[PDB]
Length: 230
Ligand SMILES: CCCCCCCC/C=C\CCCCCCCC(=O)OC[C@H](O)CO
Image (cartoon, rainbow, N blue to C red):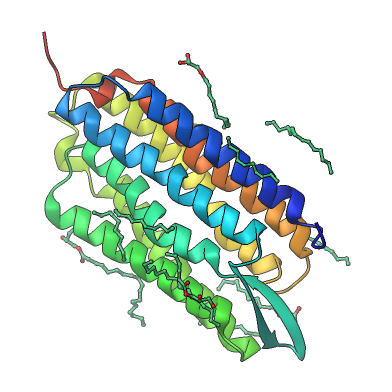
């Protein structure tokens, strides 16, 4: 409670934990193999985020990085979370549209580059270089978003209508919420430092719960996760 952002870390921990438990109960009894994949991916996402939020709340997922002549508090646990949860979210989208394996690997690999370069930027001690890493990570994000809007055209013709509808909604949610991340980083403690760490933590908490629990609620309530069966 010594850090003003503790309240948002505590709320994030609670919301990710509750979301995990809800998805775990909801997926109980699901037998359809396709739906099992979506429940597994979508329950793992907030479960991982729960552990990383808790690690930030308890102080383990925080480190001090010297730059700008200050000791800057950097929550590195965010990147350990996003390293696993962001490819999993992309996998949900890719499995919805029956994406080719080449496209899945492109997405997951670009996503690993996005998170890894974000982590390097977050830990870099030369201030100006932090924004070089931010730019590379943003380029990887833009590549991901490009693939989500222009890499699935060969699947549109054979796509079930409920699949197309649910995918279109999730793609819109993804573009809006994922785009906000580089902006928060750029203006917050890890970039220019014009927004204080407590407001940055609040912003990432709203984004993360929306991108994980909100996204999951939309996906797991849709008919698109079940194979077409009589
Ligand atoms: C001057 C800098 C030049 C280098 C900047 C690289 C830094 C990372 C930036 C973007 C990641 C790009 C991810 C690359 C993954 C592409 C995979 C691919 O090409 O997949 C196509 C295939 O047809 C299946 O869709």
